[PDB]
Amino acid sequence: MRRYEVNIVLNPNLDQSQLALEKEIIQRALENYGARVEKVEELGLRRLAYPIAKDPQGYFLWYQVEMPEDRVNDLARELRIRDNVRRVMVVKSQEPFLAN
Amino acid sequence: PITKEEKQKVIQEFARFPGDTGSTEVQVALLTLRINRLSEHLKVHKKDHHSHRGLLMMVGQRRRLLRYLQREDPERYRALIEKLGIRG
Amino acid sequence: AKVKATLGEFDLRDYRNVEVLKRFLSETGKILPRRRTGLSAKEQRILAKTIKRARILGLLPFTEKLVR
Amino acid sequence: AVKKFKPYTPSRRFMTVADFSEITKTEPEKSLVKPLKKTGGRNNQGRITVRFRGGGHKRLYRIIDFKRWDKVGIPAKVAAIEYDPNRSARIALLHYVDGEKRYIIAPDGLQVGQQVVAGPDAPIQVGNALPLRFIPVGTVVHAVELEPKKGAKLARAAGTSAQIQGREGDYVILRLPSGELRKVHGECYATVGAVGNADHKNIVLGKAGRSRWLGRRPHVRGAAMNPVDHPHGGGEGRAPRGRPPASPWGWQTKGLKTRKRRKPSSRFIIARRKK
Amino acid sequence: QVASGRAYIHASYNNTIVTITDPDGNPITWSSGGVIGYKGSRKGTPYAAQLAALDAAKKAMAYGMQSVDVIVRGTGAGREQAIRALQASGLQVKSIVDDTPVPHNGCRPKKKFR
RNA sequence: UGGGAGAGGGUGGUGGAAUUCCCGGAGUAGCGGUGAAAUGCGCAGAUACCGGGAGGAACGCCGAUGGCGAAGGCAGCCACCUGGUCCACCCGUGACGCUGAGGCGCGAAAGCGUGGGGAGCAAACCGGAUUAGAUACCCGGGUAGUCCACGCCCUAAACGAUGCGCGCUAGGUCUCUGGGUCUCCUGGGGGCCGAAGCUAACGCGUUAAGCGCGCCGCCUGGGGAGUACGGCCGCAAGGC
Ligand SMILES: [Mg+2]
Ligand SMILES: [Mg+2]
Ligand SMILES: [Mg+2]
Ligand SMILES: [Mg+2]
Ligand SMILES: [Mg+2]
Ligand SMILES: [Mg+2]
Ligand SMILES: [Mg+2]
Ligand SMILES: [Mg+2]
Ligand SMILES: [Mg+2]
Ligand SMILES: [Mg+2]
Ligand SMILES: [Mg+2]
Ligand SMILES: [Mg+2]
Ligand SMILES: [Mg+2]
Ligand SMILES: [Mg+2]
Ligand SMILES: [Mg+2]
Ligand SMILES: [Mg+2]
Ligand SMILES: [Mg+2]
Ligand SMILES: [Mg+2]
Ligand SMILES: [Mg+2]
Ligand SMILES: [Mg+2]
Ligand SMILES: [Mg+2]
Ligand SMILES: [Mg+2]
Ligand SMILES: [Mg+2]
Ligand SMILES: [Mg+2]
Ligand SMILES: [Mg+2]
Ligand SMILES: [Mg+2]
Ligand SMILES: [Mg+2]
Ligand SMILES: [Mg+2]
Ligand SMILES: [Mg+2]
Ligand SMILES: [Mg+2]
Ligand SMILES: [Mg+2]
Ligand SMILES: [Mg+2]
Ligand SMILES: [Mg+2]
Ligand SMILES: [Mg+2]
Ligand SMILES: [Mg+2]
Ligand SMILES: [Mg+2]
Ligand SMILES: [Mg+2]
Ligand SMILES: [Mg+2]
Ligand SMILES: [Mg+2]
Ligand SMILES: [Mg+2]
Ligand SMILES: [Mg+2]
Ligand SMILES: [Mg+2]
Ligand SMILES: [Mg+2]
Ligand SMILES: [Mg+2]
Ligand SMILES: [Mg+2]
Ligand SMILES: [Mg+2]
Ligand SMILES: [Mg+2]
Ligand SMILES: [Mg+2]
Ligand SMILES: [Mg+2]
Ligand SMILES: [Mg+2]
Ligand SMILES: [Mg+2]
Ligand SMILES: [Mg+2]
Ligand SMILES: [Mg+2]
Ligand SMILES: [Mg+2]
Ligand SMILES: [Mg+2]
Ligand SMILES: [Mg+2]
Ligand SMILES: [Mg+2]
Ligand SMILES: [Mg+2]
Ligand SMILES: [Mg+2]
Ligand SMILES: [Mg+2]
Ligand SMILES: [Mg+2]
Ligand SMILES: [Mg+2]
Ligand SMILES: [Mg+2]
Ligand SMILES: [Mg+2]
Ligand SMILES: [Mg+2]
Ligand SMILES: [Mg+2]
Ligand SMILES: [Mg+2]
């Protein structure tokens, strides 16, 4: 097991119930791939720096998780399988590096 | 990778006295463990020639240690290489 | 005026900190140099990578145009 | 991984044969084979209408499931990967948990023991059939229906694949094995992944007799014939074509396009092929 | 007809082409160092770019064009002269923005540019 | 044992800029190009502008006088797998070391084979100019190739033109990266300037080209010639 921060960005122009069906898919995906979800920070719609898929906004999910190191690629790829999942970034979690 | 737990089993199953961490046996054993993990990794990643240099350096290192233990103890040499299934 | 001064204590890896990180990009979207950033050698590499990530997550621009 | 031979005959020199590594069962499912009528290129009139055919190895035809919307939602187990002399792809025997058994053409990377399923809700997984409108854009796909419920017409030979490029209304945009870009209805089924046995094009027949085994009788050059036979016939000694290169029947055979202009599918061919 | 629009200055070391668009970027009219009888090296001079800009605005203002946001591309010597000309034409130059294409180290340049 | 830095390597994925092309819009008399031109392209609607699409390659800023690697070489970003290396504690083994003819493996670019891919670029090639000529430089085109996979080739100004290891002989200064008690002290790299000394001089100078020891490789006037013959390797080119 290792700790990863799974970033996901969704389709903003979705009702919260389509948005619910997508999170449930994600949920079952993290579930069936071995992740144990610690924290979960869901910032929602957010103004984009540049247009993504013709959309200046996205719905930003974030999951601190703990999964077997040898399946995070397959999981991440599986998150991308959906068309409303416009971005996914799984990162290795690190203790912070600070200034001041 | 090798984790601290598997690495200690190797030291445990090869220490001479349950505190020893640097004898020829525990070194040959520790190298043999790096090699096979690497030797297998190279069998999949055939173009990782840089890591292969690492493989040769550990092989030479173990061979020099095995050359030393055969001088000081042909009996314990033979005992070590069999427990690691090494000769070829 | 350097950015490490113009900001209190921050985490050089929170790639989600747009308010902290955007302060490290010129008016034209480029990663500022240490002569503007004020970070050290080792700090500058960390900042840029986490800037680079936030660009991929759409949190920071890769480039903005120049206004007069 | 095509196999070579040491040069212990003239022909063994260059001959190559498939490795058949992935084949797991070597006699066909008796319930799914019927006799394949060798034509020799002859039609119902008895006439040769395709020259240089015949005399090849006897074959049983394996019935292949080109629909698969036949059995929506019914999971199936890949039980065997078999040889099939009637196509370039290998074939896979599916034991549907239904108890029903069917052959599909075998996609690359398909593993005996895995499960496949057909339907709108099938996971985007190699071997699964879905209507085109539900496969993600960018996905590589094969055994594609050309028209809804008419059956898999596209990307069926060893190695081929169509790629899903975009959607427009009821239609999807496919890059066919030829590189042609074409509109195909979203209801048309396709199976995720490329056809397997992609090494099939690297086989070297190696001797004349191997073409005979395949039913391919020897081709005779027009230039080798006489003028009653062929445009290129005749001449004292050898002879260049001496006219635009023609078929036996007179039509030009270097670049002369032959697709019909007013064909209805033109409204669906986006861009002609490549290379 | 439209009142406000955008003014685009494509300007290389060869020429300076001004096209005035509408708010939607659809061109209202255009001009360049060729629309004023210069052919050749002269098409790339500052004066050429001035007349090109003046012929651009005088053609667009003749469509009711009053306000332009000035988008500037290239680096040719007729660049600054074009912006100056647009503020002197009579147009309500509401902006100047440099949108020169710059790759993030992409396609290999011609030998002339390596 | 516990830590740290890193474009070290391999695999899968993935982001934005940009160019080319296609489509739709809108729009008109040119564009492009050079020293100046022409070729080219453009009323068959180009260029310039917007929107959409495809595909390829390369990763701007960070970025450095930087880092890593044995060398060649390595630069978006993410994960996986893997190497080397450095530091601390001074815990374990007890000289187990150094080098290294052969051997083996690695080895820029180009080139070669079988597939694939092909946006840009561009040997060849064509055209335009220049010129006495111009099989060049400059311009417009342009096929290999550049890219991927696998297999070959094994070359180089493969350079620090400086083999490897150890020990010893002032410091000043800048920097990367560890440790400390964090002024500063100490390691390990990267440069600079310089003591003694070396050097034909230029220069070198704790990153020796100084003082020593070990081992290896190599030189013995220029041309002929890295050619011939032989032999080995290679598909060939050609290498040794
Ligand atoms: Mg998606
Ligand atoms: Mg963090
Ligand atoms: Mg053979
Ligand atoms: Mg033989
Ligand atoms: Mg042989
Ligand atoms: Mg097979
Ligand atoms: Mg029967
Ligand atoms: Mg029949
Ligand atoms: Mg009949
Ligand atoms: Mg009859
Ligand atoms: Mg009859
Ligand atoms: Mg026929
Ligand atoms: Mg026939
Ligand atoms: Mg067939
Ligand atoms: Mg078959
Ligand atoms: Mg159709
Ligand atoms: Mg073929
Ligand atoms: Mg046959
Ligand atoms: Mg034939
Ligand atoms: Mg013939
Ligand atoms: Mg004859
Ligand atoms: Mg007859
Ligand atoms: Mg006749
Ligand atoms: Mg005739
Ligand atoms: Mg004839
Ligand atoms: Mg004849
Ligand atoms: Mg004849
Ligand atoms: Mg003759
Ligand atoms: Mg004859
Ligand atoms: Mg001829
Ligand atoms: Mg003739
Ligand atoms: Mg003819
Ligand atoms: Mg076609
Ligand atoms: Mg000009
Ligand atoms: Mg450690
Ligand atoms: Mg158009
Ligand atoms: Mg013309
Ligand atoms: Mg007209
Ligand atoms: Mg014209
Ligand atoms: Mg393409
Ligand atoms: Mg001690
Ligand atoms: Mg002792
Ligand atoms: Mg090489
Ligand atoms: Mg090469
Ligand atoms: Mg090639
Ligand atoms: Mg070109
Ligand atoms: Mg000419
Ligand atoms: Mg010429
Ligand atoms: Mg002449
Ligand atoms: Mg040229
Ligand atoms: Mg080409
Ligand atoms: Mg290769
Ligand atoms: Mg150099
Ligand atoms: Mg040399
Ligand atoms: Mg040496
Ligand atoms: Mg170094
Ligand atoms: Mg130092
Ligand atoms: Mg002196
Ligand atoms: Mg001396
Ligand atoms: Mg002197
Ligand atoms: Mg001097
Ligand atoms: Mg010096
Ligand atoms: Mg010093
Ligand atoms: Mg000589
Ligand atoms: Mg020779
Ligand atoms: Mg040579
Ligand atoms: Mg010879």
Image (spheres, coloured by chain):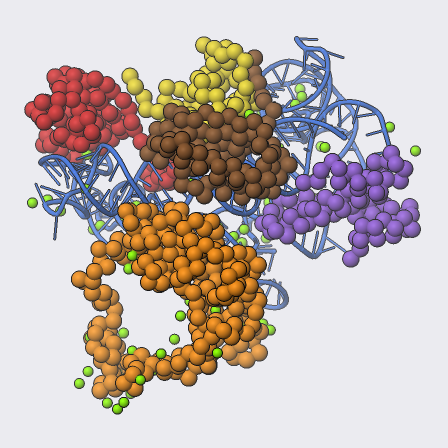
Chain colours: A brown, B purple, C yellow, D orange, E red, F blue
Position of residue D160 in the picture relative to residue E34 (left or right): right
C53 or D208, which is in the foreground?
A: C53
Instruction: Identify which residue is drawn at 59% across, 29% down.
Output: A38
Q: Which quarter of the rendering shows the C terminus of chain C?
A: top left
Instruction: Identify which residue is drawn at 56% across, 42% down.
Output: A32
Q: Quadrant of residue D176?
A: bottom left
Where is residue B66? Give x, y as percent. 83, 47
**Residue C45 visible:** no
Count of marks placed on residues: 0
Q: Which quarter of the rendering shows the N terminus of chain C?
A: top left
E24 or F74, which is in the foreground?
A: E24
Q: Is residue D191 above or below residue F96?
A: below
A14 or F102, which is in the foreground?
A: A14
Instruction: Identify which residue is drawn at 50% across, 66% down.
Output: D101
Q: Quadrant of residue A59?
A: top left
Where is residue B71? Give x, y as percent. 89, 48
Q: Is residue B72 above or below residue D157?
A: above
